[PDB]
Image 1 (tube, helix red, strand yellow):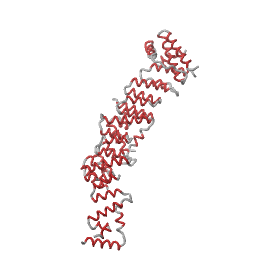
Image 2 (cartoon, helix red, strand yellow):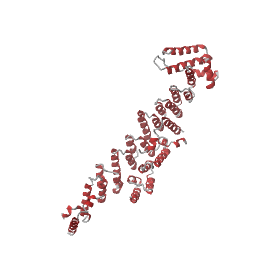
Image 3 (tube, one colour):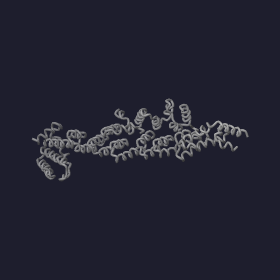
Image 4 (cartoon, chains in turn yellow, brown):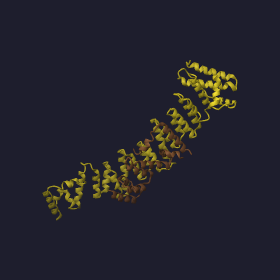
Length: 365
Length: 119
């Protein structure tokens, strides 16, 4: 058990025990004979059981039980010495630090501070951070935790200690988000940026994913945080990225989140009509605009055109997939069918010529 | 690890994370929607991550890890309460008594005296 050597050399032959008793009688009544048998320190005097305990401690190596090794000094009473020598060999543990304040408060503080290091090299940074929290080392309990690549617990501790207006918590959010940027987890990065009371970059990091659903969610987030033009740009960008597989009406309703993409809405209507034509038109277009989009009056029919003539697309060279080529052609056709009525036909014929030239240029027959 | 529930309901589908981000944006800018998802307490405010930690603690029974259960209150800061309730259920341990003198000397004395009985 705790003293295997004593119980081993205490159940010997009866003659051995008789000799031990004789030696004890000789030593008690008065002494190099008692030195050979250390266990008589249990009965002889105080100066001998100390040596017996020391022998037991140095014998407590082969069984790998440093807890009893360090507890024996508590019986001897040298708590300070065993605490000091335990950290040097990397043997300080929770058991030893339990009686750390027995010798004094400063002794306990030294014990926990030293145990923090060993827990650091023993992949126990959470326990170390808790121990630094014990002496109310609030600021230090988070820097090592985040440096050890543990941001969730660090932020939890910082919020538990520090008030929300503290400057040493937003840095945790920004650092965790920046780390997550390269990891490809843009949603949680946007969450971290949102929690850092700076949502301007949250929409951008959410949009950085590139998926149409991610683009739309970034648009909605930017609308929520008050970035109206940013949300409008995000919706416009998700519009084309939604049209690839089979989605036409989904992008039609996605363009509705802000009241600045009505021209894009009626252009994507032409996209749908031209795509269906691949399975008159100039009047069916405006009829569908009147019916579905509920825009039937010359009044706004001009101001819905002036916002569509202000944007220009690239030259649309030969090397490009036909999708955005058709999108640009249909946008120009929409501009033509707009300008054909409220003004002279010069703009209509010019826009029709522009559309036909764009279609011809990119080798598209 | 220490918070299996958070890392479980934090690696969900991308649409779920987008909805969580939308709810966080709605709650930050001003709220019964944030109550359903407790992990937003990590980002929302102080009054919510306390409830998240409490939920984690009450979920720390099925895995049989009372050490983390009692360490979570150290993060929350109620060392006295966790020390007092640990002895009643027979869960006071060497780890808990390590930070016993953090709240005070008499607290440590009570902690060791109570741990003596359980031992």
